Image (cartoon, rainbow over all chains, first blue to last red; front, side):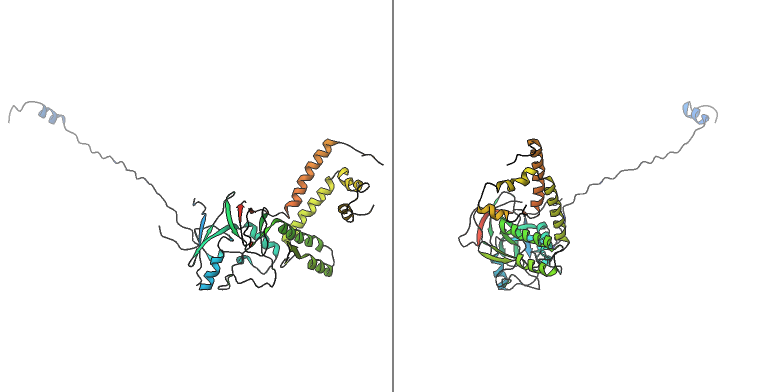
Length: 49
Length: 295
């Protein structure tokens, strides 16, 4: 506030309160594996070269 | 919001000589009116001078003063003035600014000044063609006389010849009260007095309509068997014109008087002035008194 002179209305005390909110954003990406890769990772490292 | 201030500081932006400040110091405990309430105000708004106008009417100035708020002056400093707003029912010391003599126990009213004597009292703070004009504080009978004179002049002005209107205004404007003589300045007849004249005419019409035959005949019947200076001076005003009352009905009389009281109050209000102070003390030089504030 600023002090005022004669004849002028004085400024009153003022209190202000506010709130800020956040946003949402999901991201996604798919990937797939062949069944052959699944069985190779599943079972034994054996057989022909 | 901002609560109304009780203490008001006034500062003159005009430069003050030592004589001006000396004059200000004498005015402590006097009543000064202001148009608006602030913690710090300029001297222009102080006093009755701001309303002095080419219209010059006493009635409009009386109307304006009624709406201003009254303050008492607390002690003075250099270039500053402190004013205090009184509260109803408390006890205060007040200064008799005007020439009117006060008495113990009477009621005081605030009223625009009316000139008296040589008319050379106007030394009050003339600076930059602004002047410290203060209202008068007067006891109730003088205010009633002033208002009554104004209203009678207004009513008489109707349909009377111009020259005899001048003569009536000349004889009515002067007042002798409590061994002093005063005269009303600028008794102009205009709309402000016209509205009061209208209300007075209405109230008188209703009073004449309501009054019972018993009330009308009381004076006429009394003169047949009483005799006194009061009565003979009383009956001189009336137009010159055994038995039993033609109609007796106390309930009708009661109701009729009940309404007639309301009409009489309506007529009374336009000459009544609100009591601002009631005094019970006096300085034996009449310069100051202690009063209870009301209104």
